[PDB]
Image 1: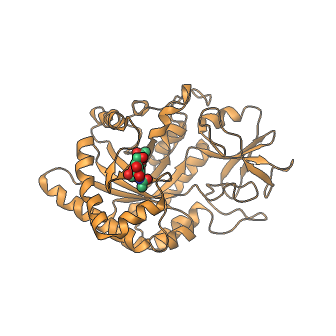
Image 2: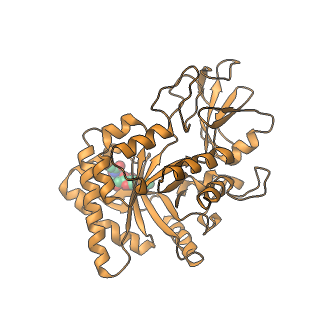
Image 3: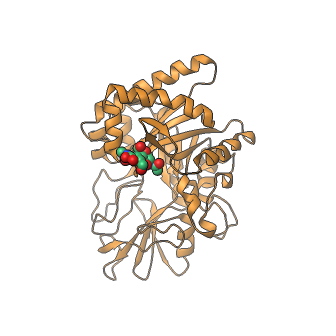
Length: 361
Ligand SMILES: *[C@@H]1O[C@H](CO)[C@@H](O[C@@H]2O[C@H](CO)[C@@H](O)[C@H](O)[C@H]2NC(C)=O)[C@H](O)[C@H]1NC(C)=O
């Protein structure tokens, strides 16, 4: 199985214990570590944070301890305008300038591949994403001729049917990618005007939940569109999503006034790291969605959908049963990477839980 794990460069800036440098990463934890995100500047791949050349070195030096570990650099992300990516991909000359820039930058910095994280292509973009994947792969096949192991090429693909349909020609892009990480953890958000889970495995029955907004639908759809199971990696979050309640109701369809209050460390309304969630659960009421197979918790006027050891283990069992290529984790710096918050004295509890199941029958 693959265990694809994202590291985010902006985690460095979180205060105190929240602060995450790549030497926090267990070199034998994941099969692949993906550093997020690279810029595109002057129509070439480029660094984003001021100290990225040092952080890339600190990540890549993990390979002296686990020579089999693979690293990738993810280009794009949500602070990169989809429109910016569209302009580069849609023109022959800019596309080529970008593609030619990628192997030398990855080699200089010690990366084994590129992850494409265009978030996300519009309807007019779908044909250009296809060309970009094809031509990037062709360039990596050519660069391999000079004697180094061929660069890997992956992509991060949203799991909502509507975004898949708009932006992605899954049958074609899957031919050229080494793996696709399916982003099966964005199925609910404050835009809705109720509580709900963002990473359910299956639909809620009871009495209100749409049939596409779950991981099983998205996996099945990707496979039906032509993505081979041996290229499909299912995303599992280590973060949870928070809401502010509009009433005393906390169950299904409970109204919300907006995102939850920021976490002490992550400092973003609507999202909490798992280490923050472990702390939140002190004094909280916990519940599970029985059909969806994922938990939530509530204290005061705050309501949190999250994943725990049990839920990620159950997701890992699913993807094994479906003969998928493995799991992706978003993100290492959102798991309890210190191992001190969740009462287990265990670094990376959720990632380790996943790995424990992938290393079983
Ligand atoms: C990412 O690359 C963009 C593209 O070059 C950078 O945006 C440019 O930055 C310079 C200096 O601020 C500006 O003059 C350009 O006009 C910007 N162009 C555009 C299209 O925005 C951006 O600063 C880079 N991002 C980071 C984090 O390095």
